[PDB]
Length: 237
Length: 300
Ligand SMILES: N[C@H](Cc1ncc[nH]1)c1ccccc1
Image 1 (spheres, rainbow over the protein chains, first blue to last red):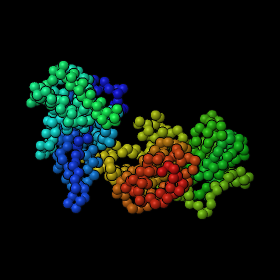
Image 2: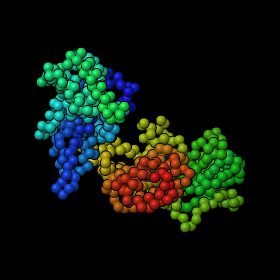
Image 3: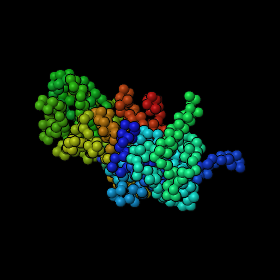
Image 4: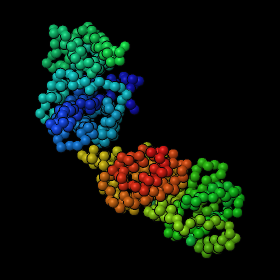
């Protein structure tokens, strides 16, 4: 069934599972034409496919060429997502294939189910959680590799950096979703928090700064404040 | 014109014959139904006065034997049987007619309703779905489950209706996932019409047989089958023009015949709204759309 607050620790058990977020697959800028009509121009996108237990991120970059000459792009984007997720599963050794795929948007269920008919034992699940994975393109290194791509490309990351050496998956996922929620609600502020102290750097092979345990507590606190704040500036409280 | 005699009527029962019905009182002197039109399959069906639970009945064709009804007090139902002694049967019938103990199949001359509901239904074709080979007539009741329902338990008592499943490898060609899911023409025309059914007459007939079992017995799996067979056509962008025209006529007469007070349970809102207003064939069912809007505008 649907993944929600009640069955949340299931994410960190030992059954392989992936989240799939298709938000950033089809991305456009809307602009005016010389005649004063409106048109779109696509920019490169990405499928966000994440193992929440290990942090392994399968970032499939969607190059604008995939849309050339196609109609109904928002609908096609969901089927392309499902095609590429199915291809990824087929590429993995049997013992690495997921037992469940959780889609962050319900409109991905039928496309993914149909592409995975060959995998009747892989459960395709929606969720009631409002996860902030759309903000993935606010992570500078992820945004950079998507925008620079000249062809379809899969890039592998660990979205937790080395955090699992010191904390549990549950805590790592909580930190990730807090960071991404903050970047989604107020990107400039969030990014200011993360980069303020210039003595804390991002390792070449990491996505996030090299905070000590104590510095992460301060960081996490500052992100919580931001989210309540912006929730104030938005609703006025 | 043919006859289905009754040995007797020992328990109070509502008897249907096709779209007609009449009440028979306990031990009322009733000995059957005469003047049944030849050339069509027919259904004779029953609802006991004391247990409206279980409507049940028998599809039969009088061209394929002499059939009669006899109540069984052990199994508690009216059973159809075949009389193989033709002279014994003619004698029984002639004597019952002479004593005017039979109701007459009450067909108005103008009225093509039953033809229109059964145009592609035959007795031999019916037995391919309802399996009991030792008899010529076929038993159906309210509770019988379909093969597809059993996949999701007694196989001998099942309705072997063609299994249609839009999210199945049969329905979806590898590499045409989006194409085949959004436009079911492949599945309709190649898999089902050319591969399994063999022709449009086969498709319409199973679709018609599904509706009639839903209507007469409240058979839920039959209702599921009827709607799936409609949806598969309406969700295909490429359908032979003769099939669309015939489908409109078929569904028109089904909607016309449906009891008004049963629409709530026998009509699936999603399928009909999708079929009449969103599907590829939203503009191809003029007669069906008109009667649905004037008779069930609430469902829509
Ligand atoms: N069995 C046929 C149609 C069919 N062909 C292949 C599978 N089903 C049918 C037609 C008419 C009345 C009832 C049943």
